[PDB]
Image: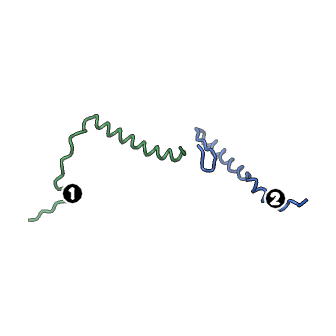
């Protein structure tokens, strides 16, 4: 089923340890996924005029 | 002497004599079971966005 943000959440039968490790890895990697406009704001002061 | 009596014990009215057979008791039990399912389905439907 979809949530408000547009993501799709899947409810499945799976082991506890696999779920815990997989979900934690998702949280860590998603920290470095940002919007393109957010990336541009970070590096806007390093772009020359030529 | 004097007499004092609890208010709620005064003249109870006769109860009904219908819907006391084994079939009617099943109907009441069935209604309670399906009424409980209604409450749980409303919760489950809310949590599943469906």
Q: Is B16 placed above or below B12 here?
A: above
Q: Residue furthest top?
A: B23
Q: Colour of chain A?
A: blue
Snapshot colouring: by chain
Name which residue lies at 60% across and 50% down. Answer: A4
Q: Residue furthest right?
A: A50
For residue A43, which numbered disc appears in the image? Answer: 2
* x, y percent for residue B34: 39, 40
Q: Quadrant of the N terminus of chain B?
A: bottom left
Taking depth in this image into account, of A26 and B37 the one nearest to the observer is B37
* x, y percent for residue B29: 34, 39
Q: Residues within 10 Å of mark 2 (few under 14, many from 20)?
A: few
Name which residue lies at 60% across and 48% down. Answer: A3
Q: Is residue B18 left or right of residue A35?
A: left
- Disc 2 to disc 1: CB gap under 8 Å: no
Q: Chain of mark 2?
A: A
* x, y percent for residue A46: 85, 60
Q: Residues within 10 Å of mark 1 (few under 14, many from 20)?
A: few
Which chain did the image draw in green?
B
Q: Residue furthest front?
A: A50
Q: Is B16 placed above or below A47 here?
A: above
The residue that mark 1 highlights is: B8
What is the spatial separation of the Cα atoms under label 2 and label 1, in whole angstroms?
A: 81 Å
């Amino acid at each position: 089923y979809p949530d408000a943000d547009g993501n799709d959440v899947s409810i499945i039968f799976s082991g506890a340890m696999s779920h815990a490790i997989f979900t934690y890895a998702q949280s860590q990697w998603n920290k470095n996924i940002i919007k393109l406009d957010d990336y541009i704001r970070e590096i806007t002061l390093t772009v020359p005029k030529q | 002497a004097n007499r004092a009596t609890s208010a709620f014990l005064d003249n109870p009215h006769p109860v009904g004599v219908n819907y006391v057979d084994e079939g009617s008791r099943q109907f009441v039990a069935v209604a309670e079971l399906l009424a409980s399912k209604l409450i749980d389905s409303s919760r489950e439907s809310d949590e599943s966005n469906s």
